[PDB]
């Protein structure tokens, strides 16, 4: 078995190897990369996502989210308070203000210590989940707006044509902006490209050990657990590395820098935080290996998780028994 300790693997494809996206994912999996739940891909030196970032300031962040925490430093939830619209140039200036900017620090480890010590005492503002792309249309390789769609993958594997579309999302971050512990919708893959700015630190639980994280979460968030049998689908709970180590949960960590891709694998729980002003682009995708994960994915039916139009068909075809109850949650 390749990668039996479930370490995060880092790949350096050549420009020739960067042509065929599906083939390269399958290669990484041949080497055991999926066992970690997360992999890093450093693009060939010849590749670029676009020519410059000099003209992005007029993108609108229609609904910036202030991420307000409750709990203790290592075990907390966050809720998202909607703020007034602002442009990316206005958000960048905010991120760089004395109230929100990254503190002085020695290295990524010192910054990580400061994040876990102090996150709960601040409410950073995240421009998350913005439909759009920063890849140039002429970028042919690993262009997250030109991937094969999940609907087409389901159709190729299972023969059933379904409605729905699959487009990317932009994320504008600042110091302390936080992504809570989650797997993807329908336990899909994700791919995330850090276009510019400061790093993003990731934490990940191997897919084979995901249920250990779920059991800990039920213990740490006991009211939430009674409310919903899949409350991590709400994307609000944070647990620190120190707490995970105290409770014996297997996990790994890595920091993504500008110009790098990350792939999350089916049922790979992940969480993390931004170091400072940045912009990322991410999208879900599928492979043949995902289908069995999609069939088994948990679902929130309490009403909180509320997701996209396109998840309907995935539930309806892969999980027909759950469909009725899940759809009640959506309506
Ligand atoms: O970058 C973020 O805030 C969150 N991204 C992801 O969870 C992802 O790419 O799967
Ligand atoms: Mg612009
Ligand atoms: Ni994710
Ligand atoms: Zn729920």
Image (spheres, rainbow, N blue to C red):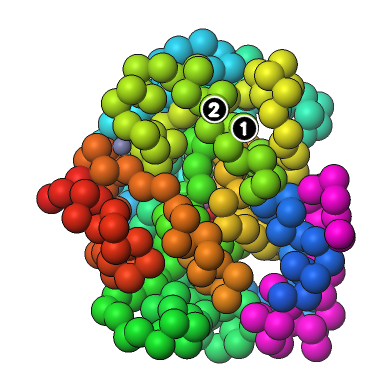
Question: Quick one: SS at disc 1?
Answer: helix
Residue furthest to the top in view is 72
- What crowding class fits label 1: few (fewer than 14 Cα within 10 Å), some (14-19), or many (20 or more)? some
The residue sitting at 62% across, 58% down in the picture is 265
Rendering coords of residue 328 (x, y %): 16, 49
Please name the residue that numbered disc 2 is placed on.
215
User: Against 181, is 154 above or below?
Assistant: below
Rendering coords of residue 321 (x, y %): 29, 58
Query: For the residue with label 1, is its CB less than 8 Å from the closest atom of ligand 3?
Result: no
Question: Quick one: SS at disc 2?
Answer: helix
The residue sitting at 40% across, 71% down in the picture is 167
| Left or right, residue 6 beside residue 62 | right
The residue sitting at 72% across, 36% down in the picture is 251
- What crowding class fits label 2: few (fewer than 14 Cα within 10 Å), some (14-19), or many (20 or more)? few
Q: CA distance from mark 1 to mark 2?
A: 5 Å
Rendering coords of residue 175 (x, y %): 56, 34
Please name the residue that numbered disc 1 is placed on.
212
Using the rendered image of the protein, determine whether residue 42 is visible from the camera's viewpoint: no
Q: Quadrant of residue 39?
A: bottom right
Q: Quadrant of residue 314?
A: bottom left
Bounds of the magenta segment: 1-25
Q: Quadrant of the N terminus?
A: bottom right
Whether 313 is among the magenta residues is: no
Whether 13 is among the magenta residues is: yes
């Amino acid at each position: 078995a390749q990668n039996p300790n479930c370490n995060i693997m880092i790949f350096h494809p050549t420009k020739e190897e960067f042509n065929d996206f599906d083939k390269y994912i399958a290669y990484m999996e041949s080497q055991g990369a999926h066992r970690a739940g997360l992999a890093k891909i450093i693009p060939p030196k010849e590749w670029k996502a676009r020519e410059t970032y000099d003209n992005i300031s007029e993108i609108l962040i229609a609904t910036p989210l202030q991420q307000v925490a409750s709990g203790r430093a290592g075990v907390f939830t966050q809720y998202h308070k909607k703020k007034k619209a602002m442009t990316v140039g206005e958000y960048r200036h905010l991120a760089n203000s004395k109230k929100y900017q990254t503190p002085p620090h020695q290295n990524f480890e010192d910054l990580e210590r400061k994040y876990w010590k102090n996150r709960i005492y601040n409410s950073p503002i995240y421009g998350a989940d913005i439909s759009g792309s920063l890849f140039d249309e002429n970028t042919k390789q690993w262009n997250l707006g030109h991937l094969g769609t999940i609907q087409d993958l389901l159709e190729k594997e299972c023969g059933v044509v379904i409605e729905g579309v699959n487009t990317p999302y932009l994320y504008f971050g600042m110091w302390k902006t936080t992504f809570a512990w989650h797997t993807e919708d329908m336990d899909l893959y994700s791919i995330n490209y850090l276009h510019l700015g400061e790093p993003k630190t990731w934490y990940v639980v191997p897919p084979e050990h995901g249920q250990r994280l779920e059991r800990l979460a039920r213990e740490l968030f006991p009211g939430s657990s009674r409310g919903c049998g899949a409350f991590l689908r709400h994307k609000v709970a944070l647990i620190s590395p120190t707490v995970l180590k105290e409770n014996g949960i297997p996990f790994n960590r890595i920091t993504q820098e500008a110009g790098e891709f990350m792939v999350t694998f089916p049922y790979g729980y992940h969480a993390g935080f931004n170091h400072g002003f940045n912009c990322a682009e991410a999208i879900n995708f599928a492979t043949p290996r995902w289908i069995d994960y999609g069939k088994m994915a948990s679902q929130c039916s309490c009403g909180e998780a509320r997701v996209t139009f396109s998840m309907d068909a995935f539930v309806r075809i892969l999980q027909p028994e759950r469909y009725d109850l899940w759809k009640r949650g959506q309506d």
